[PDB]
Amino acid sequence: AIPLNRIRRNINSLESRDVQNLMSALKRLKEDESDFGFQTIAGYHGSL
Amino acid sequence: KEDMFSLRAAFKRMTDDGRYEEIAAFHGLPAQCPNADGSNIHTCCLHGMPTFPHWHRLYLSLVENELLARGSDVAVPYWDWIEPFDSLPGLISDETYKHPKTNEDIENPFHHGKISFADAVTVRKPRDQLFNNRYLYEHALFAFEHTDFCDFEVHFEVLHNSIHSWIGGPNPHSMSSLDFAAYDPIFFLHHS
Amino acid sequence: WTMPSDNLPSLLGDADYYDAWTDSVIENPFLRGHIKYEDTYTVREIQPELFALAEGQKESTLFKDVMLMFEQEDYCDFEVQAEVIHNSIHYLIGGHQKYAMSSLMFSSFDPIFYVHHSMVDRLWAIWQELQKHRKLPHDKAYCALDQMAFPMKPFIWESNPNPTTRAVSTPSKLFDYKSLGYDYDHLNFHGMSIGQLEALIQKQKKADRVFAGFLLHGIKISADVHLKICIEADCQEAGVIFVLGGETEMPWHFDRNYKMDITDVLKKRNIPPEALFEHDSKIRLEVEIKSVDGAVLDPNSLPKPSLIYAPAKNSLTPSEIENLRNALAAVQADKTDAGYQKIASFHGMPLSCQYPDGTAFACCQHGMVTFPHWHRLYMKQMEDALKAKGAKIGIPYWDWTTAFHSLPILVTEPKNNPFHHGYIDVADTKTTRDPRPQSFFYRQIAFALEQRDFCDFEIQFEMGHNAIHSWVGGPSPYGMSTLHYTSYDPLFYVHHSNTDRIWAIWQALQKYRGLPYNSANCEINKLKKPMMPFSSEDNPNEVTKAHSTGYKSFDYQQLNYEYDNLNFHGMTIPQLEVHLKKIQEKDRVFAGFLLRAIGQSADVNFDVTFGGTFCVLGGDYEMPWAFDRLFLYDISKSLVHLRLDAHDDFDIKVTIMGIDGKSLPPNLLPSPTILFKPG
Amino acid sequence: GFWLSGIKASADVNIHICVPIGVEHEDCDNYAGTFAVLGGETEMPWAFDRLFRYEISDEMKKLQLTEDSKFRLTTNIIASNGSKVSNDIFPTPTVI
């Protein structure tokens, strides 16, 4: 009985609500300029 | 036996005159329902819709009306197939019955209907499934379960199809085919 | 990506979308992630080969790759395959571009990265579950434990946004993803469950296979490496492998070689694998390395692949009722051992044994004191016969003692029932039965229980018994009323269990009373005589022969069976004795007959009012017998009926019908004595 | 559940319970039920706007099966012609 938001699913099975949620959230995340932001966490991998 | 022979003579009087054939043509294969634009002609009876009972509720009415006007002792009886049986009812099953009035044996009017526009008679190939089937009972119980009318109707109608199939199996001019089933008297006896 | 796809799924692929909530149109967040310090967006130059990686379902190269990855039972074995297959896609969606997926340094800036990794993570997860299914370690690994123990570098640091990733920085902690708190949609590959997955893996290990082994390492730039196999020094494409890397890379060397199977690739050229060992036939495998720059091509700096030949190495609860019919059905024909007809013959008509003159006898062992053992066994023989045929419980018993309006189902149901009847090869017919009309048997049995001598008990026990073979069968030669064919009717054993049960109850009784129960002092003669057929060499059950004797077979415990409860209806055994003791108060009056062999079987009806009745079981060619003791039948109710005092003196009149319609012939039996018991 | 519509003529559909065998992939039939569909040439076309139901509970119990237990349901279609075993005219039986 694992929480609903924490289930990783096949991308083809996602309902449009899942899609919109994901998109809005990811836009907010890329836009995020904090350490929690996309630039830093993407930067954990490639950098240097 | 009296009610039976009354029904037999009433229906026979109905059959010597060309009436029941004309009534069977309402349901049967000579298509009277064309259009609305089409043009394609369809058999008139309604079998896919939820108004399936209603339609047939009328048909039986019709025959019984015209039957009682022919002097029948009783309204068209129902034979309940829900109760398992090793043999078909005496009324329809045998080809000939003994006529107490004429003191001779005569053809049973409920045995077979004639289809005169095709120069044919109805026959019945009874599938062995038909006899001693206790399945129909539980089936009916599930029909009665249904609260909504359309659910009721679909289960009710499939269940209705069951016997149509199992009574006239293989012959084309029979109860098994929607086209010619109306011409067999057993038809209304089933449908009532 | 293992499933055939004509395009990237729209969540990843679509460029722009219109949110209706604002009148604004918005860029999809999942493509072209921005790189801040490089001032450039990421790029996907998609190589067409992606399509080609999956254009055939279960026939797909990627499918086979993943299956080969799952075959591995060691974590490193699995890991190498996993990372190379991961590299394949990494290359293929963003190939031939810096700032793309094919570039290791800048791939993380492209959101699809994460989606991709979700997939491979899932793959790992699936493997782990497979590992649990194969009883191999799952939450742990025996791979490099020098790394497993230390915390990982980017996440552990004090400068980490969330405390949770600081917490589980250690590889050991991250082994089970459930403890990390998330889960996947479902863990299955294509249409296959894990049982199916492992089944098919076992299927693939059953074929001889040919692998190419590649030791890979960090070449400081990403690359795509082609494998080509040439028999005639003419070279056609064998496979492809991909490696990730960048200017800023961490120098890496693999522990072992990535494998890729050439089995089908070889079979296409119709080159037999045993000939791969042959030096006469020559085969060269050449590698065509390609940089990401393009071509470039690089000089071949990676260790050449190695060929590996892998050789294949009442109160019943359904379905309690349900199991049995089939079992009875099962033995209806074994029919070799008996299968059931031989098992039937012994009580039945076909001749069991010989006098030394070898004359036919019916090896029936009634009429003697050793009467129970033979049967009680006989159930066994029969009982064993349903052996491992789902003979999941013992033959049931129906307590005829308890008054009953009708017969018991199992043996009544007309249709599709094994208990209705038996057949008789000897007569060409199934059995016929003709039933004939406080509980009588209760009174009759209870008396038997009253007795303490075994012999005294048997006479009543046998006579109470056969009263039913009389009434169940009636006037059919083929039936339970006759010795000849009774044993044939399924009804017979079931009646028995009960008869046997009664005996058992008695034993418990004795035992309660401290009298002998697994022994018996009268007569020492006869318990010792061995019993055929159970004696016979031709009885292919070891057990019965072992107890073929009399004196064995007393302790039914080593049978080994149990009755659900030895309680007569509604009575503890201790309760029962109280009952009998209670009955015993009132003085009674009995009549006792001498009964002795006669070929026919007959019923006998009493009189003084009705005093009757009792029945005797017998047939042609039966061993003759005479009881040592009298058979007692209480007739006190009769006297009260006539108001007599055992004082006024009376004529005890009897009658004795044959089972066949006639004919009440006269004794035969002599005269009945008439005796009085206080009190 | 059975989604029925107008066949060109009348026919019998029979219902079987397919229980996969352990190792490996396998099938199929144990007789669950039977129901009929009536029709004829030149009939007014129709499609049920809902599923017809057939209770298979007892047959599932007699196989020791469950709603959660692994199995599938297949119909076999036999026209009134006698012939034939007709193929896949209705969507595969749903499990409620």
Image (cartoon, coloured by chain):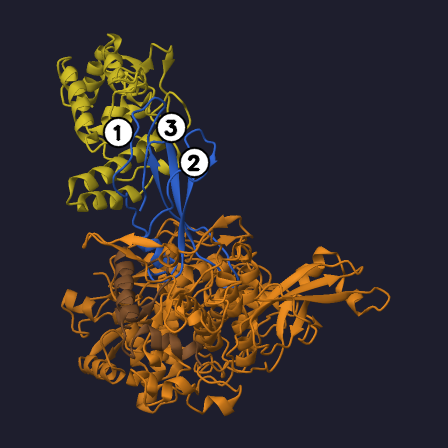
Chain colours: A brown, B yellow, C orange, D blue
Q: Position of residue C649 (x, y in %)?
A: 21, 70
Using the numbered discs, state the Cα–Cα distance from disc 3 to disc 1 in whole angstroms: 13 Å
Looking at the image, which residue sits at the far top? B17
| Numbered disc 2: secondary structure | strand
Residue C534, image x, y percentages: 56, 73
Q: Mark 1 lies on which chain?
A: B
Report whether residue C177 is seen. yes
Q: Name the residue under label 2.
A: D78
Residue C617, which numbered label? none
For disc 1, the neighbor class at 10 Å (few under 14, some 14 to 19, many from 20) is many
Residue C565 image offset from top left, x and y in percent: 31, 77
Q: Residue furthest right?
A: C280
Q: Nearer the viewer, residue D56 or C586?
A: D56
B134 relative to B114, above or below: below
Residue C448 drawn at (x, y percent): 32, 76
C634, B100: nearer the viewer:
B100
**Residue type at tag 1:** His
Q: Is residue B66 left or right of residue C321?
A: left
Q: Which chain carries label 3?
A: D
Q: In this view, does C560 lie above or below B81?
A: below
| Mark 3 to mark 2 CA distance (whole Å) | 13 Å
Is residue D96 visible in the rendered image? The answer is no
Checking the image for residue B47, the label placed there is 1
Q: Mark 3 = which residue?
A: D8
C-alpha span from label 1 to label 2: 20 Å
Q: Specify the quadrant of the image occupied by residue B66.
A: top left
Q: Which residue is drawn at 29% across and 50% down?
A: D55
The amino acid type, in three-letter code, at marker 2 is Ile
Q: Mark 2 lies on which chain?
A: D
In depth, the one of C641 and C467 nearer the eye is C467
Q: Is C444 placed left or right of C119 in the picture? A: left
